[PDB]
Image (cartoon, rainbow, N blue to C red; front, side, top):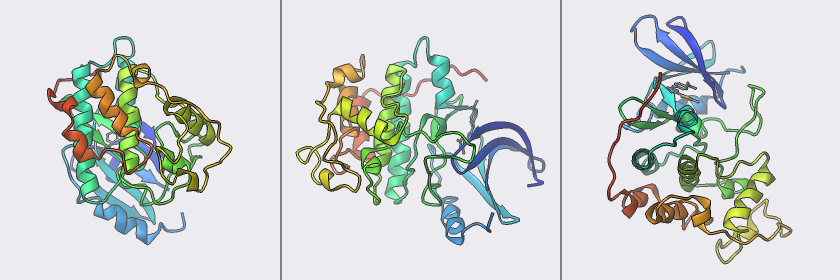
Length: 294
Ligand SMILES: Cc1nc(C)c(-c2ccnc(Nc3ccc(N(C)C)cc3)n2)s1
């Protein structure tokens, strides 16, 4: 739009490229997401528009949705840093535990809010988790999946990450729930603690087999109905489960306990965002300040 001046390519999401822009009028700076051209589906517009109402302290506010020349522009509140970069910058030392815990608690609140309104993210990842100098962390691109859909190949000619995708999605379940966001957050939680991706799969089956190698191949005992999933193959190699003490050290037992409940195979046994908030892991939760470099 003519009311925005692109300052820099802040990223390239699934539905489109994201830019840091300057409203030539208001003078406010925002992150402008342009989504590519038959005229854009009406259903999407109406769905995306509803998102303008779901406002929460831990959800990146969607200021306006601009649909001109039959193109889509999502105007979001701008934040100075994503979790990915912050992590890379913390690589040598690592993010302090008090901060990791504050971030998880805030993300969980955001999720609780979204899940209570029957809205899920479906594609949580370090790249759409934004932080500010205030010690707050926010979820970006919420509800955009129900608007369109994330494939395995992107227009940016790059590659879609499956590292945080819940097993029910990889196994073909087409009617997944809020539980998929909990799984992703769990994978992110573990990544913050170890400074290494939990399940860095390079393909769908490679992704599924890395999960299996660590948590063990799911069966009807631990996941009733798993063998009935569309893509479940009786020929899946049978891997034994591995202790969480080796999965995410030196995370304390409360943290390990919580992560374990966030990583349960059965979506129904997977702890909810609301319940996660009552976990003893957050008994001593605080809100530290990140040492950000901008
Ligand atoms: C994918 C994304 N989708 C949305 C809606 C994003 C967003 C929203 C608000 N601020 C920022 N800020 C921001 C993003 C990246 C960086 N980098 C330095 C990579 C700095 C600030 N990013 S990111």
